[PDB]
Length: 7
Ligand SMILES: *[C@H]1O[C@H](CO)[C@H](O)[C@H](O)[C@H]1NC(C)=O
Ligand SMILES: *[C@H]1O[C@H](CO)[C@H](O)[C@H](O)[C@H]1NC(C)=O
Ligand SMILES: *[C@H]1O[C@H](CO)[C@H](O)[C@H](O)[C@H]1NC(C)=O
Image (cartoon, rainbow, N blue to C red; front, top):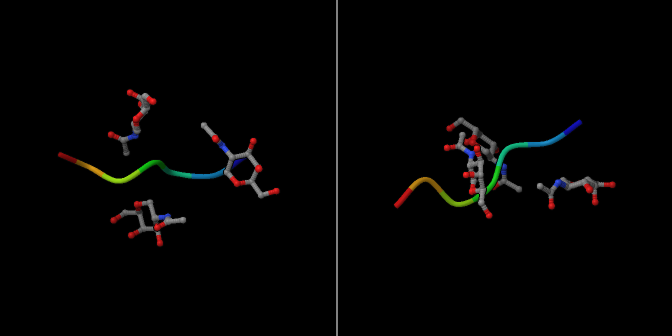
């Protein structure tokens, strides 16, 4: 699991 560029 990973986090995506929090816009
Ligand atoms: C986050 O990065 C990891 C690294 O292996 C995976 O590619 C995962 O699928 C990524 N998550 C998203 C939402 O792209
Ligand atoms: C996803 O967001 C989290 C929380 O800020 C971390 O910064 C993480 O390094 C991010 N993942 C990517 C691939 O930039
Ligand atoms: C990153 O963006 C993806 C959509 O491509 C998802 O909304 C994911 O939940 C996001 N991650 C964060 C930490 O907001």
